[PDB]
Length: 255
Image (cartoon, rainbow, N blue to C red):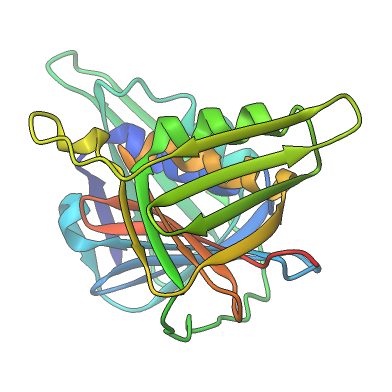
């Protein structure tokens, strides 16, 4: 077995796939000695999803040679929904593979579910995320960010994120009515995951497609917190941190 990736948590690969599947259905997953990366972006080039899973996210990880797993995520998620979470999930691939193997094993129950998925040929042209500075860097609980997006999206196809000194303001205005949610940087010491953190180098007022924010918050299951980095000259970066790695959404604002 050239590739043998045993997830620490079976739910993790399932929750990772959730960040991708409803946006771009066919995604190339590249495996290397140092772990797994994946990117997805449609023709509009407006939203880019970028994953990185490091070795430490696995119980055992081994990848002899670089492998690209071209996967239809619709199929992959059906199969992944066959797992129990009380299951260990092992990805198994061989030299120049036609198929990926998913090996669900039940602890102490003597059950082995082995699934195989035929791989697809996908032209994944990669982009090294060119690293830049952001005008504002923000972080809040992911479930809080999610409720904000879900709500304002009831009112508009556009959601505005406005950063001024010590103020984060999410705004939407549509036909039925308007919505506004303002949050202030708090530092909770008893419970730091609930903290609201803000660093503003320059104020920003960016407007985003609500469909894309709705795509992004599909990553909320992956991390207690989402990091938002905003730019008046480049895409915003919405990131969910993994134990080893991240799911990044790069989103281009509107005019």
